[PDB]
Image: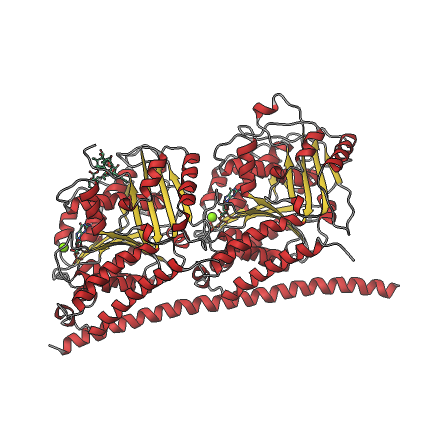
Amino acid sequence: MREIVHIQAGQCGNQIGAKFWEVISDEHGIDPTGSYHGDSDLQLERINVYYNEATGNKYVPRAILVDLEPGTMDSVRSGPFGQIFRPDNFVFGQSGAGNNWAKGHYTEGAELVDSVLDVVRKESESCDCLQGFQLTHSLGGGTGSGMGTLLISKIREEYPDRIMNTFSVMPSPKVSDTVVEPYNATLSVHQLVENTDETYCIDNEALYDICFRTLKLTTPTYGDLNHLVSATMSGVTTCLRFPGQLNADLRKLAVNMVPFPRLHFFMPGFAPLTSRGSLTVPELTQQMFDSKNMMAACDPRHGRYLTVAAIFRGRMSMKEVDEQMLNVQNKNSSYFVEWIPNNVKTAVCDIPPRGLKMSATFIGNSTAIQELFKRISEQFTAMFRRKAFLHWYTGEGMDEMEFTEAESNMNDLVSEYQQYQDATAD
Amino acid sequence: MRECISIHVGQAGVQIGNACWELYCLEHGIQPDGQMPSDKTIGGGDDSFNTFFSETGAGKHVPRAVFVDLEPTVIDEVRTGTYRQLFHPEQLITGKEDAANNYARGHYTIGKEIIDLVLDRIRKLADQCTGLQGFLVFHSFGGGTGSGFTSLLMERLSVDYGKKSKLEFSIYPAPQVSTAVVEPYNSILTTHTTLEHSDCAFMVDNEAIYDICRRNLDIERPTYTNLNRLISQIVSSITASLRFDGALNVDLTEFQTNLVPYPRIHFPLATYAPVISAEKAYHEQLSVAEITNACFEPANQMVKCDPRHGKYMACCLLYRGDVVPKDVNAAIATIKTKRSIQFVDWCPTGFKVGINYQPPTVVPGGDLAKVQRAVCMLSNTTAIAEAWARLDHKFDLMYAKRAFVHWYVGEGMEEGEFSEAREDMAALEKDYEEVGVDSV
Amino acid sequence: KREHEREVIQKAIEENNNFIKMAKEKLAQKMESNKENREAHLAAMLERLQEKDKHAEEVRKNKELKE
Ligand SMILES: C=C(CC(=O)OC)C(=O)N[C@@H](c1ccccc1)[C@@H](O)C(=O)O[C@H]1C[C@@]2(O)[C@@H](OC(=O)c3ccccc3)[C@@H]3[C@]4(OC(C)=O)CO[C@@H]4C[C@H](O)[C@@]3(C)C(=O)[C@H](O)C(=C1C)C2(C)C
Ligand SMILES: Nc1nc2c(ncn2[C@@H]2O[C@H](COP(=O)(O)OP(=O)(O)OP(=O)(O)O)[C@@H](O)[C@H]2O)c(=O)[nH]1
Ligand SMILES: Nc1nc2c(ncn2[C@@H]2O[C@H](COP(=O)(O)OP(=O)(O)O)[C@@H](O)[C@H]2O)c(=O)[nH]1
Ligand SMILES: [Mg+2]
Ligand SMILES: [Mg+2]
């Protein structure tokens, strides 16, 4: 069919990647041993997109696990679905990256990238018609941030006409203590603006706020944050994994969502979200468009929507979905740019998630995403103002010009979002 | 002799082709395995239905059709569907990667890899014809294959089959069932590129069909299956003159003479009646007068526009079923006294009538009631330019910001092709204004 | 009248052949122009990426010098 190759890099990348494979394996009826045990042929119709079929009627994720230290991938292999992954697709070093983008991008990460590229080629060469790649990683560390973006550039060199998609976890002081994350994130975003086609912005600040304020979790853990991510990743990949008319492949999704090449950073959302200590189509619609349900710490009412994709899951009235989707658009027409007519697209999938009878997934390309990049830029400049902690990076051969260039590119990206937010038709 | 080759391009063209060929088989008594127990001419013949069906020595009646799509999943349903035995595998052509709702990919990047094979297969069908009359091309405006590959195919057909007639059934986009933001781009690009290569194009506004299904068939949320069964009835009415013979039967090319006054002005407005549920038809017998009156209700048009705000250049009535000229003439006389029908000053005001006697039929399990008589009106009205205006306006909104244009340039297209296409549409709109201004 | 009759049908033949010829040449130009444009865009992309590869080697070379 149209195969996707999945890559997970670094600690965060491998942990959210493992949770993604657990969730969609349950949806497609695949057990930890790779055998199908579902009850619906719809589970197998597009299984080729993410799984290879091996000997013995077993399904193996088209997934590559990358890290510069063995720790996280050891726990994945010893995890719930650790036995489903191809053992030859574990590629790891020993030196680690020390939360250093330069180490991931230029030194230790560059030492290992050729070994990762070897397994990418084997998975791609066994594809009937490869459509592209999806990468899971964080931007605040060293391996997922530095080596992840190095992988993106090197893969793009060998597959320049394929779609590059990432799930990029943005750092926040509410989750991580390390001080150099604004540096690592700014250097990474500079790469993502140039070399990816579509990026889901998974903001750890939004994940924390949802767990704390909405879910009433006093001390959110990484498991709590990743629980939100796996539900979101299952939602935004539903159109790729099940028969459907809308955004059924990575390229059609990109053509619908990206009106300008650099503005390809999506705000994802999910509904319902409520604490455990306590549903209609109209309520699903209003929640999915509410700022509290967004996985990027941005208020969409502070900007305007370029494009939106909405996916409803479960058994429900399509007529009601159609009415409510046009209802929210007409009532909030100020927040959708008028010079992109019919910029909101809606899909409905009959098979709902495990524990819910109805759910909704939101994918927004909003100019309000600049609030996320402004937050990172503010933290970057507060440190770069005083050349703080730079020796970790210049010691690997980097020059200060590369920081200045990365900062200017992200400020340029912010200016671009504001330009199209202010643009008018008449 | 007088054979017609149908070409179905992309998902919309293929799925509509499925509906049309299923309906044709029911109208002609052709079984899903291609056998036709009424056709005593085994392996050949010059019957009227032979314009659309060839015949093998084993008695199979094979559609003179090619199905083409740049991805396989839609045509794969034909290969395994109820009418799989109807087609030979060579008539069903698929690639592995579609045009991604991008005209540039259907016309250039992906389409160029399969165009030669498609032409070879069309040539195989043409070689079996003793007097090929032309082609019928089914496609969407909005899809990357329906827009881009169709225009490439139409360009190549003009080279390989000179001026042999090419007619279109084109699916005009509607937001209720649209899948791509860039459909206005694809629509303008393919309309510009195909304009000089098409002799006659019947546009089908998905929103008009959607509204008819909701209003007349009580369907809450019509699907493509709902839309395509209605569309196939309209297509069948238009092609009925080619597939059946009779003494009141007027050939489509004779209607075409009246419908195309200038080469570019070749977009007839189709209106069809009656569209009625079985629960409503069970009481009423709708007369010739009632179905004829319904042809002048704008709610029954296949393209949303207001002919009361334009001028007519031609009016054709294609009846099928239990209809005699006496009742047609009385119905037309009533219509002219009570209806807003203004012609341009340079064309005759009469109505051209054809009657095909075999009654219409319906696919089992459908929503349309089986009626004793139906009618399709084909009019050439300046009001159909309203459909171009709506598309041109959505084009202008996005192109002024160059929104999504990088997807087309990335596949080798130039910005000049956008403006060249848009200027051709502007001239076409001005052409429709000019034809409707009184002489001096 | 006979010579006018032959001139009419010769004109019809010439117009049809010229329509075929011009449609053939225009399509050949479009496909060649499109092929050149798309290959030029891919080449610009790969050259930008190769500029990044050399920069990765200057960084590694610069780290080695400061040891
Ligand atoms: C895979 C897992 C868990 C895991 O092991 O990951 C590997 C999973 O959760 N999948 C689900 C899914 C969703 C979309 C696509 C695919 C799958 C689903 O099918 C399910 O089971 O939801 C779970 C999730 C819940 O925990 C819970 O949320 C949380 O407390 C929580 C804590 C931290 C982070 C996130 C949530 C959940 C919420 O979250 C959801 C998702 O609904 C939150 O607000 C939502 C409203 C729900 O009513 C409410 C409140 C529940 O009360 C409900 O009783 C329940 C269900 C229906 C749980 C209590 C068991
Ligand atoms: N009436 C009708 N319209 C359809 C059908 N299928 C698709 N469409 C319309 O066609 C347009 C989308 O084009 P498609 O035909 O699906 O795309 P395609 O030709 O296959 O081209 P690509 O998939 O981009 O390669 C939208 O306006 C749809 O509403 C159908 O079966 N019936
Ligand atoms: N949501 C989420 N974020 C994580 C997880 N693990 C690490 N992070 C974030 O990732 C950043 C650290 O990057 P890390 O993955 O440890 O660096 P690397 O392993 O060298 O690539 C911090 O900002 C963390 O908040 C996780 O499991 N879930
Ligand atoms: Mg860590
Ligand atoms: Mg298609």
Task: Pick whichever, A270 or B305, lies toward us.
Answer: B305
Q: Quadrant of the C terminus of chain B?
A: bottom right
Q: Is residue A273 left or right of residue B41?
A: left
Numbered-mark total:
0
Seen as rendered, the residue at the extreme top is B283
Q: Is residue C42 above or below residue B229?
A: below
The colour scheme used to paint the residues is: secondary structure
Q: Position of residue B198 (x, y in %)?
A: 64, 54
Task: Pick whichever, A227 or A107, lies toward us.
Answer: A227
Task: Pick whichever, C5 or B382, lies toward us.
Answer: B382
Q: Position of residue B298 (x, y in %)?
A: 63, 39
**Measuring 13% from the left and 57% from the top, which residue is drawn there?**
A69
Q: Position of residue B42 (x, y in %)?
A: 66, 36
Seen as rendered, the residue at the extreme bottom is C65
Task: Pick whichever, B377 or B154, lies toward us.
Answer: B377
**Measuring 40% from the left and 67% from the top, which residue is drawn there?**
C42
Q: Is residue C32 left or right of residue A164?
A: right
**Quadrant of res A82:** top left
Q: Is residue B68 visible?
A: yes
Q: Is residue A283 above or below residue B420?
A: above
Q: Give ligand 3's quarter of the image.
A: bottom left
Q: Is residue B264 visible?
A: no
**Quadrant of res B289:** top right
Q: Position of residue A405 (x, y in %)?
A: 26, 70
Q: Quadrant of the N terminus of chain B?
A: top right
